Structure formats: structure tokens, C-alpha cells
Image (cartoon, helix red, strand yellow):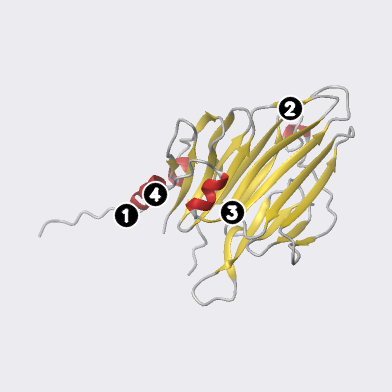
């Protein structure tokens, strides 16, 4: 039972679940829902017939988002609604959770004006006797079937060794999944004109994976290498979420070597039905 908070700027309307801090819906006010609509375009969404979420949290031995340590952390929040105020160029949305040992975990969303790159920052204060072992993760998950409603989509990533790469949702659904290591890099879900991406900011070697979550859900994500938070200290785990138009210039400012060019070419080609006519 985690409430839903509203987080608004000029370009994004996010709903964030307070149990785990997953982004459950993202609307884009600069883009109409369809031709002639009042409504903004819906990228991330949570509904009975379609889900598309940017999930994140702290896993590893001592991470609270690790199911073995119990249910996802219920964060406390100041308000239910945050809105970029006039004259202000940045919005901060901090949420705090306190462990059953006084360990404090602060997850903070940082939005900037006109900016589709949302910073997602943790601070972990260890108030106990042993080091806390923690991996952060970013997952993007999506229903394979759109709502029947009665133009292609896929997963991508890049690493220092992988200039372009792409997984069709079919492949993921076939249990043929990515499982690799990447220092830096990024993972994304693509559609036409719009993209979602997680870009970790750390010094380690991430695990980049795709996953069949079953019942029609595909996923791509990263799990950053485990870090120790000493009894002394407060640790920080940072990543950036792109949630917006597929503007390469803007994305590449946040992820160097962002080039989707060859990914789109593959996904465009692969999603077109085959017809070989009989001779005549």
C-alpha cells in the first residue's frame, strides 16, 4: 500500500509509486496524444491492458528492494504533488525510508526545466555496525501486446564494446536473453519518435540484461556492481532516466556515444511482415 505522487514540469507529468519509487506513468505535454487532441502523449503507463514503467531500486545483500530482505521500501514524502514553480529551473522530489536498524535510504528525483533527463539519486546512511552491501538497478518493463484498440518497438543498449545492439521483444519472449558486463553504457526501450533509457553513473562494471517476466511482459535493465557502505559513512548511487522524444543530440549529452541509427534500421526491417507473391 504505497501512494502515488504527481511530479510536474513543463515537459513531463510523472506518477511515482512510493513503494519502491517506480515511475508508473509519464505524459509529455509538448506532444499531443494524437492528431488534434487536448491530451498529452502517454509514454510510460500503468493500466489493466498495458504497462510500461521505469523501475529502480537498491538490491544486493542489504538492499531493501531485494525481495529476500522483505517487501519494497515504503518511502515517506513531504507532499502528494510536486510542480516546477515559475521562475525556478529545477525540481527536487526527495523520499526517505528508515530501515529496521536506523539505516536511512533517500531516493531523490531531480528534474530540470525543459529536460527529459531525470536524475535518480540515492543516499544510503549506514548507522549500524557492519558494512551494507548494495547494488542499484534500473529496469524498463513493457507489455508486448499494445491494447488491441478496436510502427515498431524494441530494446536497445550500448557498451564500450557494443556500438549498436538491439533485442526484439519476441527474442526476449523466447527466453533468449542478454546477460553481459558494461562499464558505463546504457539500456533503452525504443519506439518511433520516443525512447526510454537508464544511464547508470558509477565507476564499476554493470550487469546489463534483458528478461522475460512472463505473462506478456518484457524487460531490459542494469544491475550495478555491489558497493560497500561502511559503518562510518553515507553512500551514493546515481543514475539518469531518459523519458522523452528520441532526439539524439539531447540524449547524447546525457549518454556519450548515443547513436540509435542502426537500431532503428534493424527494428524497422524486422517488424515488417514477409510477403513473397506467387509468380504470375
Element marked by disc 1: loop
Q: Give the residue pinned by disc 4.
A: 267
Residue at x 45% of width, y 57% of height? 192
Viewer-proximal residue among 124 and 268:
124
Determine which residue is flagged by label 1: 273
Identity of the residue drawn at 57% across and 58% down: 50
Q: First in sequence: mark 2 or mark 3?
A: 2
**Which of the two residues, 185 or 222, is positioned nearer the viewer here?**
185
What residue is rendered at 48% in x and 37% in y?
175
Q: Circle 3 — which element?
A: strand
- Marks 4/3: CA distance? 19 Å
Query: How far apart are labels 4 and 1 at the CA level?
Result: 12 Å
Question: Is residue 194 found left or right of 237 in the rendered image?
Answer: left
Q: Position of residue 139 (x, y in %)?
A: 61, 43
- State which mark lies toward you, 2 or 3: 3
Assign a secondary structure to mark 2: loop
Q: Are marks 1 and 3 in contact (CB under 8 Å)?
A: no
Badge 2: how crowded within 10 Å, few (<14), some, or many (20+)?
A: some
Q: Position of residue 278 (x, y in %)?
A: 15, 56
**Which numbered circle lies on residue 61?**
2
Q: Nearer the viewer, mark 1 or mark 3?
A: 3
Q: Residues within 10 Å of mark 3 (few under 14, many from 20)?
A: many
- Taking the image as shown, residue 37 lies to the left or right of residue 122, namely left
Image quarter of the C terminus: bottom left
- Of 66 and 222, nearer the camera is 222
Q: Which residue is mark 3?
A: 243
Mark with earlier residue (4, 1)? 4
Q: What kind of element bears circle 4? A: helix
Amino acid at each position: 500500500q504505497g501512494k502515488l505522487i504527481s511530479v510536474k514540469t513543463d515537459v513531463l507529468d510523472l506518477t511515482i509509486n512510493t513503494r519502491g519509487g517506480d515511475v508508473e506513468q509519464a505524459l509529455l505535454p509538448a506532444y499531443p496524444k494524437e492528431l488534434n487532441s487536448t491530451q498529452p502523449f502517454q509514454l510510460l503507463e500503468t493500466s489493466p491492458q498495458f504497462i510500461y514503467q521505469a523501475q529502480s531500486g537498491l538490491t544486493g545483500r542489504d538492499g531493501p528492494d531485494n525481495p529476500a530482505n522483505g517487501p519494497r521500501p515504503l518511502y515517506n514524502v513531504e507532499k502528494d504533488a510536486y510542480v516546477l514553480a515559475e521562475g525556478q529551473n529545477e525540481l527536487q522530489v526527495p523520499m526517505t525510508y528508515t530501515d529496521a536498524a536506523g539505516n536511512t535510504f533517500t531516493k531523490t528525483f531531480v528534474l530540470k526545466r525543459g529536460d527529459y533527463a531525470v536524475n535518480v539519486n540515492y543516499n544510503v546512511q549506514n548507522a549500524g555496525e557492519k558494512p551494507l552491501e548494495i547494488s542499484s538497478f534500473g529496469q524498463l518493463k513493457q507489455s508486448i501486446t499494445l491494447p488491441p484498440h478496436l510502427t515498431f518497438r524494441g530494446a536497445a543498449y550500448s557498451t564500450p564494446d557494443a556500438a549498436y545492439a538491439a533485442y526484439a521483444f519476441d527474442t526476449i519472449a523466447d527466453n533468449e536473453n542478454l546477460n553481459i558486463s558494461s562499464k558505463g553504457g546504457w539500456v533503452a526501450m525504443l519506439q518511433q519518435y520516443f525512447a526510454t533509457a537508464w544511464i547508470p553513473h558509477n565507476d564499476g562494471t554493470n550487469n546489463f540484461y534483458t528478461a522475460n517476466l512472463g505473462n506478456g511482459i518484457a524487460a531490459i535493465g542494469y544491475k550495478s556492481q555491489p558497493v560497500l557502505v561502511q559503518p562510518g559513512q553515507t553512500g551514493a548511487m546515481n543514475s539518469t532516466l531518459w523519458v522523452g522524444p528520441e532526439i539524439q543530440d539531447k540524449m547524447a549529452a546525457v549518454a556519450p556515444h548515443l547513436d540509435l541509427t542502426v537500431d532503428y534500421g534493424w527494428l524497422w526491417f524486422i517488424s515488417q511482415p514477409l510477403l513473397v507473391p506467387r509468380g504470375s
